[PDB]
């Protein structure tokens, strides 16, 4: 759109391409997403209102000549690239902690307004030079080829629950937490059943004891194999006891048992939280 000069393509998305761009009438540099219903219009207009330091700012919605552009604040790296960059050494735990804590704050905000992300993944998490981490694409899922990753998907989604809650985002972030610690994807599924079966092999096949109502889930099958739960000391070493306590609460099968973002903020793991600055080279 005429008011913006593209500077570079900064990624492919689900809904379209993302450009780094410069506004001519503000001089501001940004991230310009090109998308493809008034419902979608109203939903997005809602998002322009949920402003939080840990949510990528939606600057402007441009519904011109019947295409849709979303103008966001620009950030210089995402967490996936940073992870890949930190791999030989791993992200220091104090930064993992700070990142988790900030994200939890962003979630507690979104969720308190009844807005879910639905699709948390490292690629949707964006970082700056100042030690901040922000959720991007928040709200688009409920508002609207390269394969979409299943790795972070909550089990109730995989089992065909149509009415997810805020807990699906806690799950995702817990998968993200585990991955930052270990330097390997927690559950790298390459189909819905592989993804489910990886969850099962690690946390154990859910039943009515741990997850009441699980056997009445739409895509649940009495024929699922019955794997034993592993020890968390095996899953994410060498995360401490507080860290492992927290992760287990984020990965609870029953979404009603699963810790909230707000309760997670009070967990003892955060007793000593700080705000380190990452070494990122741009
Ligand atoms: C320089 C770069 C890290 N800045 C980016 C990239 C980016 N890519 C999107 C691709 C599609 C994904 N589902 C989500 C991330 N998006 C943004 C924003 C936004 N919004 C701001 N900076 N960046």
Image (cartoon, rainbow, N blue to C red):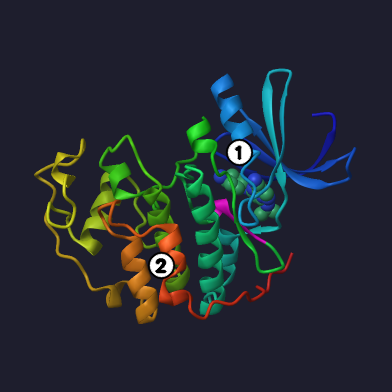
Q: Percent position (x, y) of residue 199?
A: 27, 56
Residue at image location 67% in from the left, 74% down from the top:
277
From which residue to which does the magenta span run?
Answer: 123-127
Image point (88%, 42%), residue name: 26
Q: Is mark 1 within 8 Å of ligand 1?
A: no
Q: Which residue is drawn at the image coordinates 26% and 50% (left, top)?
A: 196
Distance from label 1 to label 2 (Cα)?
29 Å
Question: Quick one: label 2, few (<14), some, or many (20+) residues within 10 Å?
Answer: many
Query: Furthest residue to the left?
Result: 222
**Mark toward the viewer: 1 or 2:** 1
The residue indicated by pointer 1 is 47
Dominant SS type (magenta):
strand
Taking the spot 62% from the left edge, 74% from the top edge, the residue there is: 275
Q: Give 135 or 228, whichever is nearer the viewer.
A: 135
The residue indicated by pointer 2 is: 178
Q: Secondary structure at mark 1?
A: helix
Horizontal side, residue 227 vs residue 68: left or right = left
């Amino acid at each position: 759109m005429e008011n913006f000069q593209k500077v570079e393509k900064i990624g492919e998305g689900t809904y379209g391409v993302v450009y780094k761009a410069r506004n001519k009438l503000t001089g501001e540099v940004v991230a310009l997403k090109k998308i493809r219903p008034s419902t979608a219009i109203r939903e997005i207009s809602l998002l322009k209102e949920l402003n939080h330091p840990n949510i990528v700012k939606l600057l402007d919605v441009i519904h011109t000549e019947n295409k849709l552009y979303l103008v966001f604040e620009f950030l210089h790296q995402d967490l996936k690239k940073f992870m890949d960059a930190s791999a030989l050494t791993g992200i220091p735990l104090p930064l993992i902690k700070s990142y988790l804590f900030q994200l939890l704050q962003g979630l507690a905000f979104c969720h308190s307004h009844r807005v879910l992300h639905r699709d948390l993944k490292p690629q949707n998490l964006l970082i700056n030079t100042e030690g901040a981490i922000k959720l991007a694409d928040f709200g688009l899922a409920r508002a609207f080829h390269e394969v979409v990753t299943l790795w972070y998907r909550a089990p109730e989604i995989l089992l065909g629950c149509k009415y997810y809650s805020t807990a699906v985002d806690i799950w995702s972030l817990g998968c993200i937490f585990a991955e930052m610690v270990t330097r390997r994807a927690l559950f790298p599924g390459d189909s819905e059943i592989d993804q489910l079966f990886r969850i099962f092999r690690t946390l154990g096949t859910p039943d009515e004891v741990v997850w009441p109502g699980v056997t009445s889930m739409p895509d649940y099958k009495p024929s699922f194999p019955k794997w034993a739960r592993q020890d968390f000391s095996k899953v994410v070493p060498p995360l401490d006891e507080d860290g492992r306590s927290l992760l287990s609460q984020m990965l609870h099968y029953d979404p009603n048992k699963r810790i909230s973002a707000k309760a997670a903020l009070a967990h003892p793991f955060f007793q000593d939280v700080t705000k380190p600055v990452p070494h990122l080279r741009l």
